[PDB]
Every structure is written in C-alpha cells, then in structure tokens.
Image (cartoon, rainbow over all chains, first blue to last red; front, top):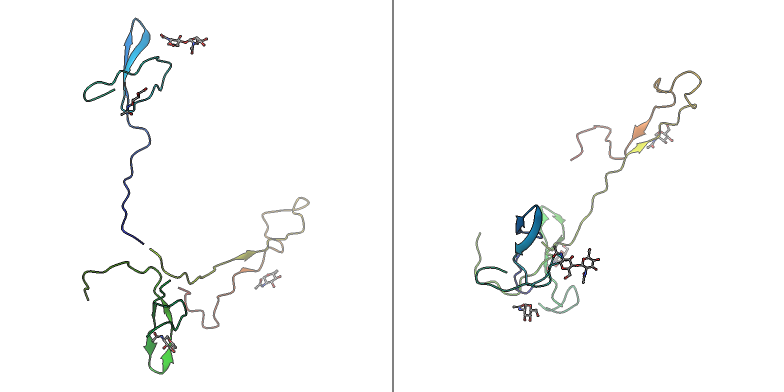
Length: 48
Length: 40
Length: 48
Ligand SMILES: *[C@@H]1O[C@H](CO)[C@@H](O[C@@H]2O[C@H](CO)[C@@H](O)[C@H](O)[C@H]2NC(C)=O)[C@H](O)[C@H]1NC(C)=O
Ligand SMILES: *[C@@H]1O[C@H](CO)[C@@H](O)[C@H](O)[C@H]1NC(C)=O
Ligand SMILES: *[C@@H]1O[C@H](CO)[C@@H](O)[C@H](O)[C@H]1NC(C)=O
Ligand SMILES: *[C@@H]1O[C@H](CO)[C@@H](O)[C@H](O)[C@H]1NC(C)=O
C-alpha cells in the first residue's frame, strides 16, 4: 500500500541461566524486565 | 483516478483482455503508490 | 498481494445413508452409492 516495512522478531530467544548448589540463581537475559521472581535486573554492557 | 469504474480517461484500475471477438474483464487488485521502473 | 478475488468452490456430496448396518453389515456399502460433485462433464475431461 504505502511503503512502510516491518521486521519479524522471534517470540522466544534463548536465555542464559546460572545454577549453584542445586538451585538456580541469577540470569542473563535480553529484555529489560524481571521474567522470574528475581527482584533486580541490572543493565550491563552487551546484556541484562 | 475517480471512484467510478469508468472514472477519468480512491483509484480503481481495470485491465481487460479480449481474445478474438470475446471481451473479458480482469481485476487489478493492488495498486502501487509509485512505480519507478517497468519491465516486460 | 491484493487482487480482486474470483472464487471457485469445489464441494462433494457423500451420502452414505445405509440401512443402519448393525443387523447384518455396515462395511457392505448398502445405499452407499452416489457420492458426487457437480463439475463432472459428459465428456468428463479432468476438471482443473
Ligand atoms: C526471590 O525474590 C522473591 C521476592 O523478591 C522471593 O519471593 C517470595 O517467595 C515466597 C515463596 O514462593 C512467596 O510466598 C512470596 O510471596 C515471595 N515474595 C514476593 C514479594 O513475591 C523469592 O523467594 C526469592 N527467591 C530466591 C531464590 O531468592
Ligand atoms: C529499564 O528498566 C528500568 C526499570 O525502572 C527503567 O528505569 C529504565 O528506563 C529501562 N530502560 C530501558 C532502556 O528500557
Ligand atoms: C473493460 O472491458 C469492457 C468490456 O469489454 C470495456 O467496455 C471497457 O472499455 C474495458 N475497460 C477499459 C478498456 O478500461
Ligand atoms: C447423489 O446420490 C444421492 C443419493 O443416492 C441423491 O440424493 C443425489 O440426487 C445424487 N446426485 C447428486 C448430484 O447429489
């Protein structure tokens, strides 16, 4: 119709998580959001 | 350009192809906003 | 791509309608007969 263009991002990109002493702790993500019950999402270079 | 199917000699484009003595009507459908090049 | 839709409907009329089939046989194809779709030609050239 007009000329606008749209990208198609995938729904669920893989997330990197960490475990220690047989429990999960911390998580490397891509979105500035607290997906799990973690109380803080420290923005860091190249990742959250 | 005009809304009416006949319009002027909302934009409606009709391509009609006739074989022999039979005349047929075809539907343009999508119409480009601007065309910079044409190939055939 | 927008093109003013010109339709074609292909429909088929299976009418198995047997006389129950639990008393003698269901897989015996009773009153199984005509199942057809209007598009057949007397010449019966394949309908594409
Ligand atoms: C992570 O933090 C959350 C809250 O910051 C902890 O949540 C509590 O967990 C219990 C057990 O499910 C719930 O009954 C409470 O309602 C939660 N509180 C809130 C505010 O949601 C959670 O236990 C922490 N987990 C770890 C592993 O640190
Ligand atoms: C990330 O989330 C925090 C949460 O408060 C917000 O303050 C910040 O503006 C967000 N940044 C981006 C780039 O979304
Ligand atoms: C479309 O076809 C009809 C019937 O042949 C014809 O009258 C009409 O002029 C055609 N439209 C054109 C050429 O734009
Ligand atoms: C097909 O068969 C059924 C039952 O035999 C009948 O009602 C119908 O008229 C037949 N023909 C068509 C075109 O459905």
